[PDB]
Image (cartoon, coloured by chain):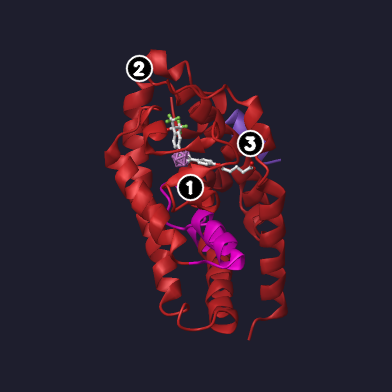
Amino acid sequence: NHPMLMNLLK
Amino acid sequence: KLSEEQQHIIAILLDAHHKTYDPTYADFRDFRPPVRMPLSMLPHLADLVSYSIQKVIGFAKMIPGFRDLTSDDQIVLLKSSAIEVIMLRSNQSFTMDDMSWDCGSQDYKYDVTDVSKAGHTLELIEPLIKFQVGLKKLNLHEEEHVLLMAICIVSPDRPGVQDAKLVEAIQDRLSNTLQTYIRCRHPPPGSHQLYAKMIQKLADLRSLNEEHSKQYRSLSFQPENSMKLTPLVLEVFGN
Ligand SMILES: [O]C(=O)[C][C][C][C]OC1=[C][C]=C(C2345B678B9%10%11B6%12%13B96%14B%109%15B%1172B932B437B%1285B%1363C%14%1527C2=[C][C]=C(C([O])(C(F)(F)F)C(F)(F)F)[C]=[C]2)[C]=[C]1
């Protein structure tokens, strides 16, 4: 449920 | 007694901070502009927090051992610590003179009434100021300041952590680095009880965290206010 977090975490 | 691994850890965290903290405040002209003359400052300060989250994430990625966590745990830890790390890293621009965060210019110099103009009350702002004062008086070495940020992020007791075992062992290497640093490179009397004082500041931040999320949920339950937030702030802080 966290698309932008996971993208930013590489 | 500062081992080679420990000096390594300090080198990486110093560099990770300098790569994610720009003391020129160049990017501030990209935010929605500040208005003072109605939650006037909420667009500009929500933009600042959303930017700051991206910087905190880039710092967290460089903390040694963090990438050996699962993405679920990494998400847990960043969701819980984001506002605390932002408050802690804001101490660098805080000036005890006029009790304001002086990020370069007067437009980008924020006092307690600016924070009020984003929807927050002195229930939060009063402990927040005394937090920034007490940290300012600890006179921390930059080495200690970046170790503290790392220890904040990698906490085993955050709600929903899965591998508390691995999280605890990662934090332990950082706490032992900090304790050994204080002992070896921070002369008395400023070293007196310094580790305990720094851990007290993390406790101050847990309380500040709880109050932030109460006033955030109140704030963002009004859709007029949600509209002024950013998509990243919403995903991290909720709804
Ligand atoms: O790389 C670089 O350039 C280095 C950059 C240097 C970094 O400078 C700074 C970054 C952040 C801060 C702040 B200091 B305290 B005081 B309160 B907290 B820190 B953050 B702003 B101000 B207000 C803040 C704040 C505002 C808004 C909300 C919100 O609750 C809301 F907006 F009010 F709703 C929300 F939603 F979370 F944003 C929560 C908290 C000051 C300086």
* Mark 2 or mark 3, whichever is nearer to me: 2
Residue B76 image offset from top left, x and y in percent: 50, 44
Q: Are marks 2 and 3 in contact (CB under 8 Å)?
A: no
What is the magenta range?
B139-166
- Can residue A7 be spotted in the picture? no
Q: Is B136 positioned to the left or the right of B54 in the image?
A: left
Q: Based on the displayed image, in which of its 4 quarters is residue B157 positioned?
A: bottom left
As drawn, B109 above or below B191: above
As drawn, B119 above or below B187: above
In the figure, the shade used to draw chain A is purple
Host chain of mark 3:
A
Host chain of mark 1:
B
- Real-space Cα separation, disc 1 to disc 2, in angstroms: 24 Å
Residue at 37% in and 49% down:
B129
Residue that badge 1 annotates: B81
Mark seen at residue B54: none
- Real-space Cα separation, disc 1 to disc 3, in angstroms: 16 Å
Mark seen at residue A6: 3
- Real-space Cα separation, disc 2 to disc 3, in angstroms: 27 Å
Please, what secondary structure does the residue beneath circle 2 have? loop
Q: How many residues crowd mark 3 within 10 Å: few (<14), some (14–19), many (20+)?
A: few
Q: Are marks 1 and 3 in contact (CB under 8 Å)?
A: no
Residue most extreme to the bottom: B1
Queried whether the magenta region covers residue B165, the answer comes back as yes
Residue B16 image offset from top left, x and y in percent: 69, 54
In the figure, the shade used to draw chain B is red
Residue B52 image offset from top left, x and y in percent: 58, 39
Host chain of mark 2:
B
Q: Are the numbered discs 1 and 2 placed on the same chain, yes or no?
A: yes
Queried whether the magenta region covers residue B193, the answer comes back as no
Q: Based on the displayed image, in which of its 4 quarters is residue B28 positioned?
A: top right
The residue carrying mark 1 has its beta carbon less than 8 Å from ligand 1: no
